[PDB]
Image (cartoon, rainbow over all chains, first blue to last red; front, side, top):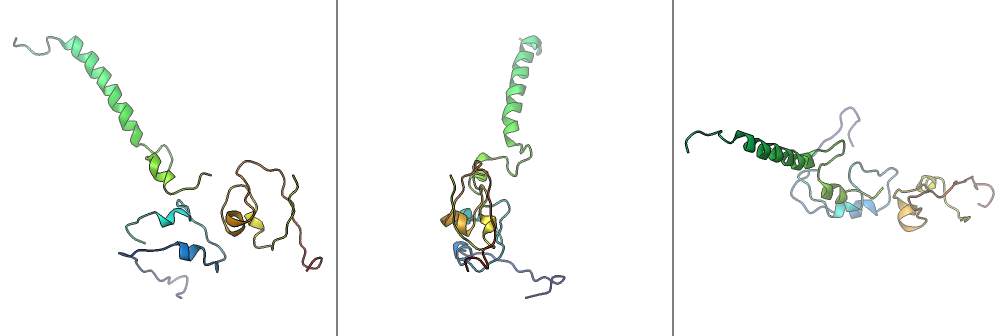
Length: 49
Length: 49
Length: 48
């Protein structure tokens, strides 16, 4: 991974993402959302991540 | 048959009544502080708390 | 009502009214409204 002052940034487009396999695969200390609920990400449909 | 604004007293009560109903619909697109001005979109992406 | 159970210390934030997580979505779920008081202490050298 990159350094905090030199943080890597990439773009996600044109895919069928699945956020349930990021949510339920529990290996994470903090997992919090802002303005979105974590369970409704299965239904949402975005322009860019 | 020729001179317009011969009935300018009756046109005002139509213009006043329509400008008020016009401003009532246009206040449905304000946020008033929230993240969205549309009620379906905060029910499609947030938890009931 | 006094409900008694054991968890670890990482999941002690999961017991509060109205939030998600591992315990709250599948085990002990507290309704939004108030319950009362929530009391906790350590059992490292008492029961383990």
